[PDB]
Image (cartoon, rainbow over all chains, first blue to last red; front, side, top):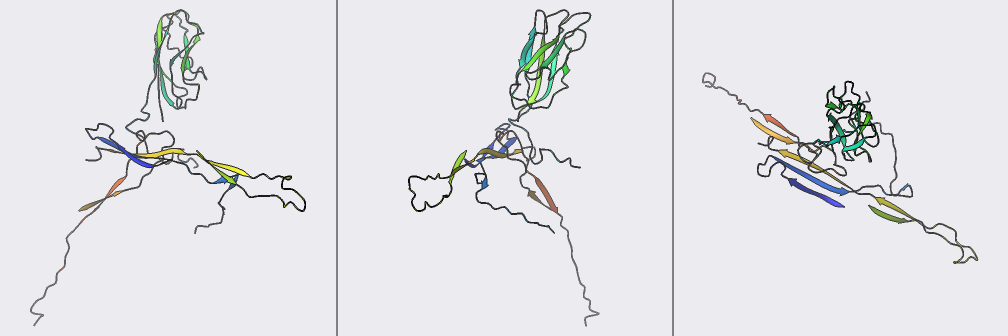
Length: 52
Length: 140
Length: 52
Length: 52
């Protein structure tokens, strides 16, 4: 919905540069494809990894 | 041992700006006439998404008797005695300015955004005065 | 939010011998998937007490 | 001596739903490393009693 955009602000007094804030903002949504209660394109697999 | 770090466990942390640098709401309800237990009045009104920090209750002398018996309750529409229960600061013998001790750090729900003052016990001899409430809170 | 459709395959039996192409109906399957979208961001402050 | 700075990465939580880009601050981490410097040497002598 919105690409990440940046912006800055002079907070306390713009003449007496005592404070400044930078920031970034985003509108996005991520979801796994699901139809009729089923995974659309993923096969999950569980294996025993010992981690030695 | 399973006492982990809080539901807060990852972020940075607030300072100068438009956040929830803590706030007040103040009202001065004026009682007059005779004072029975059929009294109710809003003094102030609160947000929805806010957590209370502390309530200060200062009143005048409302029952000038040798044995005073006036008694106040401070709360909202859900719980009539949520902040103060049997305050007795309006009596002419005791002292005023009692801070709140019950129900402090809790998120306000919908329909509970108006602070009422209800009279719990009848006044033996009603005088004229006023009651002040200051409620501190903040927002996310 | 944003809804995405899906059509399945076709399912029955080949109408053997005598049967119409007007008598014996099929439906075609159809489903949905909706992705919700939210705002999010992050910011950093810079003072002057820690800058000179 | 010579001092060298370092900046870390960024740390918190994405300010979900409603929150400003002016309310909820971060610091940026910063560190130092200083290398000290010293003199050093070596020498060799040659006579004439051991040279003719």
